[PDB]
Length: 218
RNA sequence: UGAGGGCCUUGGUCACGGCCUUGGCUUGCUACAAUUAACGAUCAACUUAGAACUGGUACGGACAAGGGGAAUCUGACUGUUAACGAG
Image (cartoon, rainbow, N blue to C red; front, side, top):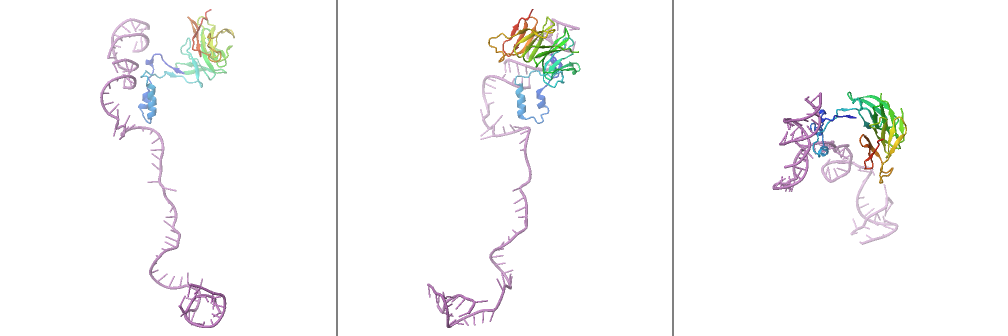
């Protein structure tokens, strides 16, 4: 996991040339030309991360800030575990182990819960200091939380159907699908991104090029 | 002559540091030379296959198995006292 700064002046510069130019020990001509081919689009500013938090043993699928602390860094990876981080010390604080690879993580700070959607077609609820939502039919790719209601979260999955869930229940309330005449259910139909926008509703996008907007307002 | 970086700076903005704007090493497009680059640089490969010292050759000097020579009679028998026979 990388820890970066939005303001680029606070982060150390990285120079691709200096690796092959300052020592210049046994850099081959072909390697030099290959390096040169990577800066054909001008010389844009390049920066190095403020920190590199490294404890996961499998590809990390998502990372989020704490909705209150800004120092707690919950993240999920393909190594069935949820790790919380101390961004000040860049260290892993606590680890939780799930049975399946986790693909998305979302937070419900108003009731202190973490919803992790896994590759086992379900979303597990954890207390970062329980119940699990089921009903999907493929990988749960992304999650989002309702802005006005604190008990509702939306989930998009690789089966092409978004679903809205109440936390207290275990079944979806509404199952949004892709409204398109040219989409096939299992050929080109996936939801790679879902978003709860407080003004326009639910935005879903994926394998089908169309970006779909659904009301999702009372 | 356009682009991207670096040092400058000018105002408004949020408690030395952000946000929005103002004017002055790399590469892109064009114009005249060079096309003997038939040059130069760099990375990578490369170590000495030789062993053996056998004899028969022509020559120079002594041994080599061992008493010799001639002619007639005689036995199978050619082209000059023909030859031959361990007679």
